[PDB]
Length: 151
Ligand code: NA
Image 1 (tube, rainbow, N blue to C red):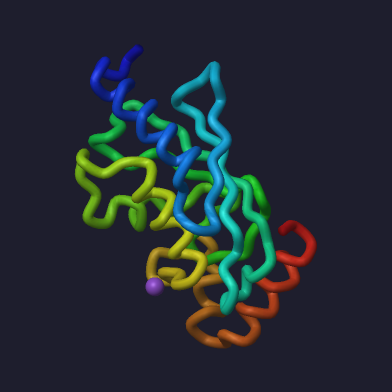
Image 2: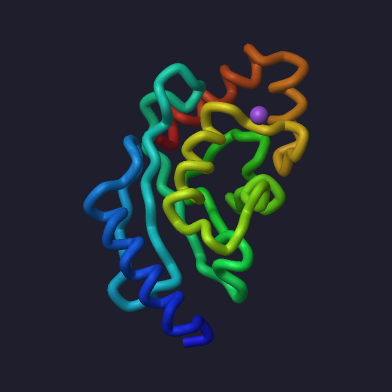
C-alpha cells in the first residue's frame, strides 16, 4: 500500500508470530481486511492497581511505521498517567529508544510494562500523574475502582 512491500511482509509475519507466541498476558486478534489496525488485549498485571482487568487496546500502523512507533489506544477505560482522554498512549514514552528495527512485539511489551511502572513525568492524565507522585494510595484506589468497572 503506502507501506513498502518488505514492511508488509515483515508486519504480516510478525503478527503471525504474535498470534502463536505472544508475550505472557498479551493476546492479538488480527483483522484479515486491515493489516494496519491490530486489536490486542493485555491482562492487568498482578501486583499493580490494574490486577485482574483485561484491557482491550488497538495499534494503528501510521504514515511512518516503522520509522515511528504505531499509534496506540486503550479501548478499555483506564486511569493511568500516560493514557489521555481519548485513550491515546503517550507517543513520547513509546518513542523512547525507538528505531525502525523495532516492531509490534516491542510496542506491546512496552505498554504491558507501563501498567506496572507508569511514567508520571509524561502525563497525559494530569490528575493521574499528580496523584501517583503525591498520594499513591489514592492513585491506586482510583485505578482499582475503574479496573473493577471496566476490566
Ligand atoms: Na516510570
